[PDB]
Image 1 (cartoon, rainbow, N blue to C red):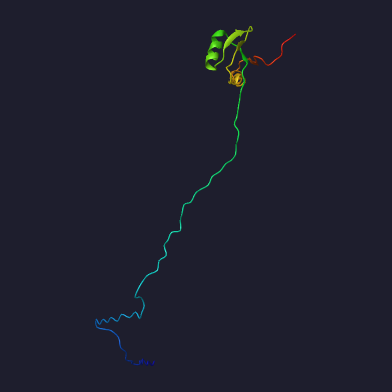
Image 2: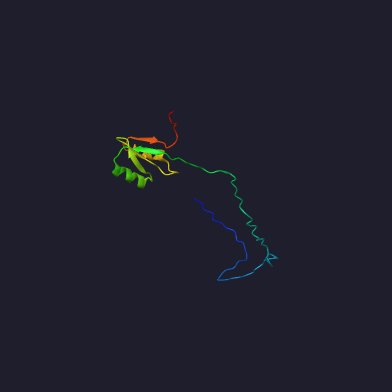
Length: 130
């Protein structure tokens, strides 16, 4: 049941009682400032685009006749639209004359596509008899 609470005593200096002290010291820290290398190395010379691919063009020349299964009323209607020329019929087909440069062969593809029986004829492709 013993208790020996002994403590030492030392002296020291320190700011107290609302005591304030300022002592700024740099020691040749910073006196001047200068260091920047901004040149922005960017120059636009040219792109450069070349093809050199071609040296030619398409082509398509054809003209003969087209047997369309329809009456005169239909012939003239096609001759004006497609640019053909209603000449005559062969009983159940009107042989129209397509203009020079028109793909009469392609036209028949638009007709038969719906269900029209037609025949691609020519006006000087086959040979004549004796």
